[PDB]
Length: 622
Ligand SMILES: [Ca+2]
Ligand SMILES: [Ca+2]
Ligand SMILES: [Ca+2]
Ligand SMILES: [Ca+2]
Image (cartoon, rainbow, N blue to C red; front, side, top):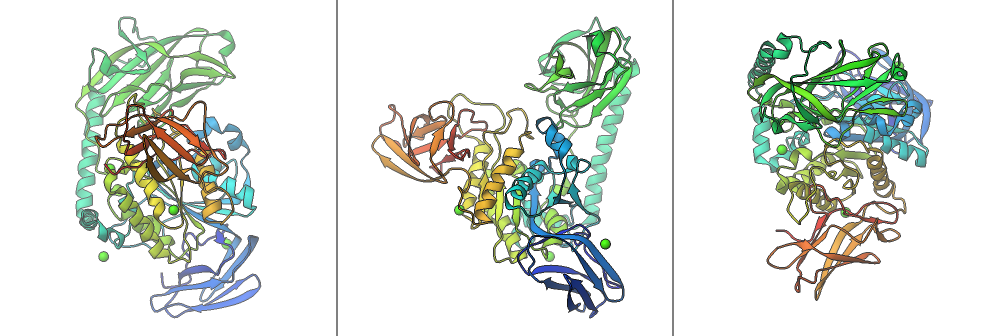
């Protein structure tokens, strides 16, 4: 702006500023306006440039507060409740976004009690811009941890801050700038994208609003028409199958969990209805009951008797619905589920809870359900996600903050690049260098999360695009002032959004203690350093062994070894100190070792004694 003093949304009441450094305050005014600032009983002045931009440095201030900052020129603004602490930018895709509410079943006591005015959070609006690097955002405010705010905070960011605040005893500010499903190249500026012509040219393409409008309108009409035709052809809607009294005794049966592709319906999309009678004891009546219905591909509405109780519109959230008192009746009760499936295999994910819960008591809902096809629809092609295109997230969600002094970044991203791992080390290195060039800071620690275990286990040695993504992450640790949290032990085979985010936060906090704070503590997880061939044995040396390596719950697992024919076989591995000796009787001249090299390497059990799991790795470049 240029009519009067205006501050960025980030520079606002309740904010955290970075401690112990000359610290930037910035905003807009009239051109050449002289701005008077009073902070900690000292006067500052600065003059705006000819475009009405102004900036200065307040004196280095130690942790604590509160402080006011009074700003005056043609108008006046007071910032209240400002504190000094460590300010962290928190970014990535879905696993950085995932809120405390989504992981609540692991952390109910934490959520109920959360109250810490020194942990403060700033949610950045999730949007893009292809035409320019933005200087502000549309809205946002700093919030403190309270029982009323905690549920919507990023779980990883919250546990990271909880750890650091507990140890360092200073305020922690968290700026959450994340976007589900986003690939790394969405988060890189035009300058960084010059190294990636394919992505540079794509960003340029999307400067055309008419292109955007035509894509979005086409996608919207396809989706709307699909849902409308579905509803108009669904025999369950036409014939009121949601009714508790509908006689479904003639329907066929399938087990839940499971997918209807295994029934005579086969691999059809559209809608399928499910019914079950449940026996409810008298002592469960007139009380609130919880219904867990696992995870469903893609969407569901659930009815209990004649009452709609809830719906979920996409495949990723767990189904956790409440059944208020008064809906269940003595004995004879029906649950009805209408499942909508746009694409892929519709149904109920395995290894998830399907039950009613009251107190510590449960009624298991796994087993036989009656089912019938509602409407067979052709698969619905997914939208073009314009918000995943190169550059747009840098421009609208990172560029606004490049004047903010930070302690560092935490980053959890890569699932959306796991299909193209060969470029990822270079792409992610480019991102880190790109941001550092915008902040221009004496140091800028960049801490990131290696992808978790996911998908099915595998009995024999094999290659894996997820393992290749994880390895690209591990190799990025060559970049200065970086650290990594390993998560191969705390993911879930059947869920890309695992609930254990406290261990993620704690592992990032360990990295921060070492990298950002220069503490004399183990840096995190054991990392492959070097190999030596000696006869039938390869000796692996590790960094970050702390007080020693160990194998949990058995001998060293998930090591494989290969000779020059590149055929890996499960190897024996023995720990000697900070080294692991890997060998197979079946291979006389080994040239390569792999550890935990799978989508889901259950059995990879190497830790340091400080509790941090070794990174998976490979010695080869095949
Ligand atoms: Ca104020
Ligand atoms: Ca340009
Ligand atoms: Ca991709
Ligand atoms: Ca390093």
